[PDB]
Length: 396
Image 1 (cartoon, rainbow, N blue to C red):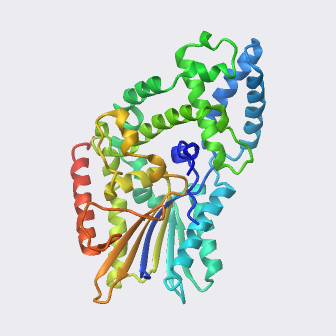
Image 2 (image 1 turned 45 degrees about the vertical axis):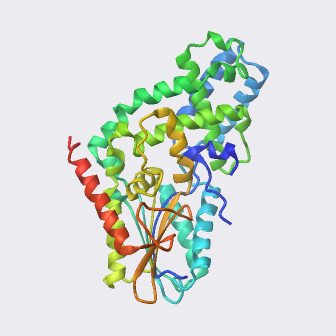
């Protein structure tokens, strides 16, 4: 809601969200989590400590060093864990689902959930499922997780050409030029350090970006401490535009990526269609399929679906933030739900929810937000055919 929250990008907490379908196809990111890496924290601490050693800290810098050390102790042994906020995010998504559609989860409905091998995704799964079961203990639940789901939930680690692009592709120099252009370190470091002009641009920029990283993740930890006022609103705006661009080029439909980051999600799109077709035909009689994974799963998946705006190909880096916004796609606990309906004449309609808001597809319908399942499935199969055609070029 607030501009400052939006500027946390994919580190933004799930936004406030406070007739009846026969099936629900779901994919959700884990809820809000702790930082996964101590790298930014340690870099901020090294710079401040070393400055404290040469009498180079302002008053606010000494206070900042004290605070950073406290965070280091509070984060210790918590890295990457689902936070209590992340638990409550899952409980709200689950709870709104069962209260919006209780017949679907009535009687002895059958649901299945899958997660990656990552504990925060599993703990998110269970927070979600415990809510379901508390509301209806007569639910039939199948719960599984692990590397057997790597191909549909973890494709971003398995595609060699994509891993190479992610680690050393042409988006890197663009991203680094964008950072140098958008971030002025010296005004920020003046708050904390005497003589910030004595710092080289490279270390000054690594310090500032590391500091942003620490401030950006703090609201996801449930620790009652905040660091947003380390920076002005305009500085957060600029930092966000750089992180938004990094996500868009490394994981979404930027021209520099040639759709390789998007194409790799096709097995999940294929899996989504198959599980719906099996429910529709009666081969399966699950009332819902839930899947718990990561931003790296959701972002290319939403782009591959073609949910409008999310697969735009912007040639100019400075224009991306106008057209593609990562906090509207992959906040914490980001999720995609497909709701299936059968009408009076047994026709099948699908409604697509991104973060619980109706999403548009570039096909026609006479009753938005409801789309013809036949037309939608035909469109998704074309998306998969295109993704495979893309992948045939980058076969390494």
